[PDB]
Image: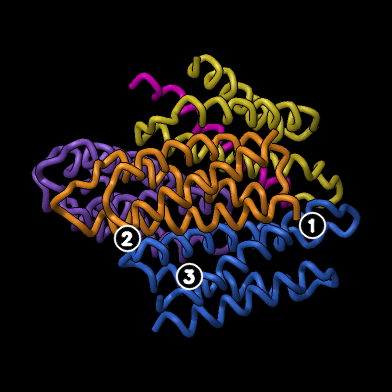
Chain colours: A blue, B orange, C yellow, D purple
Amino acid sequence: QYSEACIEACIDCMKACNHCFTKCLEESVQHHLSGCIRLDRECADICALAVKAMQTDSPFMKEICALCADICEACGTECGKHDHDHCQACAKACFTCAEQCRSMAA
Amino acid sequence: QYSEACIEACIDCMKACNHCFTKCLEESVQHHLSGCIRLDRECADICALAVKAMQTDSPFMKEICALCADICEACGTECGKHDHDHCQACAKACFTCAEQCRSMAA
Amino acid sequence: QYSEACIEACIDCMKACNHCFTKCLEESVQHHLSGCIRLDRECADICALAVKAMQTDSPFMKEICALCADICEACGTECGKHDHDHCQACAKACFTCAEQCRSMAA
Amino acid sequence: QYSEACIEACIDCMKACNHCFTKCLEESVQHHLSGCIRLDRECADICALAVKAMQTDSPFMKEICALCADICEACGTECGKHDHDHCQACAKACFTCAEQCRSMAA
């Protein structure tokens, strides 16, 4: 139960990254800074792995959470440069998951 | 929003399958009917893929949800034969996710 | 060993779909028919799950392989409409994996 | 092409970890030191993510490869304590993938 807050934060960050992925693929004219798409995919995959590792009580919980913190920091810093509302929600959820994973792993 | 109930049910089924995986790996003397472990892993992986496909609005949402319904039916039918409380919770969450995916895909 | 040809074909299809994903994200002016990007991601994920299910001898091998056949048929039919060489390689690997999964599952 | 050797080594390590998972779940009387099963699952999942990140040319290639090196070192050190041939093959593939990921990331 000591990682449940980080589990719920990473599930919300998964949902925000997948929503930003889909709503960036729907729009066409901006090109949405395609590193945002690649980073949203890699952030959703590392957050899915972090949820899987925290829910299974793995002995590599802190290292996966530190890597997820780094990827979430980069995904938030790249998605915050956009004007769309889904990208701002993705950046806010990524920074929340990043500060949660940095406060978790020590 | 028309698949959000199935998304939350599959996230609860992911958590229940991973918890049954970990608590079946912790105990030693029963051997916990190792098909339960393999089916809990495959059910958690197909439910993670189903959550990823429903959150990304994929064109193959119904087929992944029907496969997730079949795997959740089998995982519930195999985990319901056990006396442990985590296995009964896993079976109840798997049957809830199974009836949700069967009511969803049509 | 009776699914090893399908395992190697799905690994080659994973590599081709990820390469088409990356080389579609690199180019900017075409927009690369963003359904190609979404289908390449979903095809790489279902082929990773199919490789995981065939390598673990799961009881749901044929259903995952039939779903992988459907997704590979759709990804090949959508990537074959493009002029880029990586998209043509992705379409050829997807149709090879599709005919291998359709000849496998029966 | 500068990570293709690590990609093939991680694919062989995925196959060895999944084979050790399945052949540890088949046998019953040893109990196969269930941390071996959990570590084989987590090693196969981090190696699948490392293959996905190296095949997609992600900007977080070195960090995922260093985490995969740590998990492969631990999985090899835990699987080398067993007498079964699949566990020894899993340990040899894990140490090969570990030295490849440690020679790769710098």
In terms of depth relative to the viewer, which is nearer, B46 or B4?
A: B4
Horizontal side of B59 relative to A105 (left or right) equals right
Q: Residues within 10 Å of mark 3 (few under 14, many from 20)?
A: many
According to the picture, the residue beneath numbered tag 3 turns out to be: A67
Residue at screen point 61% across, 63% down: A14
Residue at screen point 63% across, 34% down: B63
Give the label on residue B105, or none: none
Question: Which range of residues does the magenta coloring cover?
Answer: C1-26
Q: Is residue C11 above or below residue C25?
A: above
According to the picture, the residue beneath numbered tag 1 turns out to be: A23
Indicate which label's residue lies in the foreground, 1 or 2.
1
Horizontal side of B89 relative to C31 (left or right) equals left
In terms of depth relative to the viewer, which is nearer, A38 or D23?
A: D23
Residue A58 at x, y percent in the picture: 33, 64
> Decide: marks 3, 2 in contact (CB < 8 A)?
no
Give the label on residue D71, or none: 2
Residue at screen point 60% across, 45% down: B100
Describe the element under mark 1 as helix, strand or loop.
helix
- Asked if residue C5 lies in the magenta stretch, the reply is yes
Indicate which label's residue lies in the foreground, 1 or 3.
1
Q: CA–CA distance between discs 3 and 2?
A: 13 Å
Q: Label 2 marks which chain's residue?
A: D
Residue D18 at x, y percent in the picture: 32, 41
Q: Quadrant of residue A8?
A: bottom right
Of the residues shown, which amino acid type is indicated by label 1? Lys
Quadrant that contains the C terminus of chain D: bottom left
Q: CA–CA distance between discs 1 and 2?
A: 35 Å
Q: Label 1 marks which chain's residue?
A: A
Q: CA–CA distance between discs 1 and 3?
A: 25 Å
Of the residues shown, which amino acid type is indicated by label 3? Leu
